[PDB]
Image: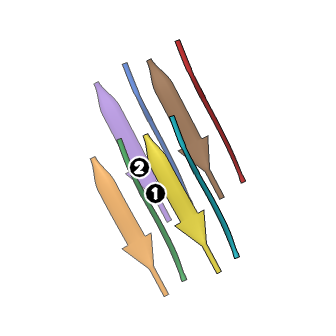
Chain colours: A brown, B blue, C purple, D orange, E green, F yellow, G red, H cyan
Amino acid sequence: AGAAAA
Amino acid sequence: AGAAAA
Amino acid sequence: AGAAAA
Amino acid sequence: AGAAAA
Amino acid sequence: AGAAAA
Amino acid sequence: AGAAAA
Amino acid sequence: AGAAAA
Amino acid sequence: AGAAAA
């Protein structure tokens, strides 16, 4: 599971 | 902007 | 399962 | 999944 | 500009 | 997962 | 900007 | 500008 934002 | 998965 | 938006 | 905007 | 993927 | 904006 | 995974 | 991945 993983997530990223900018 | 963002993204996620599992 | 996964998702993304911008 | 992928997304982009500008 | 923005982008994301997962 | 990855994301970027500018 | 930030990201996390497990 | 910003970016992240995991």
Q: Are marks 1 and 2 in contact (CB under 8 Å)?
A: yes
Front residue of this view, candidates G4 and B2 = G4
Extreme residue toward the bottom, this view: D6
Q: Which mark is residue E3?
A: none
Q: x, y (%) of residue A6?
A: 66, 59
Residue identified by numbered label 2: C4
Vertical position of residue B1 compared to residue B2: above or below: below
Q: Residue at x 60, y 72 (%)?
A: F5
Q: Chain of mark 1?
A: C
Which residue is labeled 1 in the image?
A: C5
Identity of the residue drawn at 43% across and 40% down: F1
Q: Is residue C4 above or below residue E6?
A: below
Inspect the image, locate mark 1, and give the three-letter code of the amino acid beneath it.
Ala
- State whether discs 1 and 2 lie on one chain: yes
Dot 1, how many residues are within 10 Å of its Cα: few (below 14), some (14-19), or many (20+)? some
- Within 10 Å of disc 2 (Cα), the crowding (few <14, some 14-19, many 20+) is many
Q: Is residue A1 left or right of residue A6?
A: left
Q: Quadrant of the C terminus of chain E?
A: top left
Residue at the top extreme, as displayed: G6
SS state under label 1: strand
- Which image quarter holds the N terminus of chain E? bottom right
Q: Position of residue A1 (x, y in %)?
A: 44, 17
Instruction: Tell me the CA gap for discs 1 and 2.
Output: 4 Å
Residue A4 position by quadrant: top right
Q: Does E6 appear above or below C4? A: above
Q: Residue at x 37, y 18 (%)?
A: B6
Viewer-closest of E3 and C1:
E3
The residue lying at 52 percent from left, 11 percent from top is G6
Tell me: B2 left or right of B5: right
Q: Amino acid at mark 2?
A: Ala
Q: Position of residue F6 (x, y in %)?
A: 65, 81
> Disc 2 on helix, strand or loop?
strand
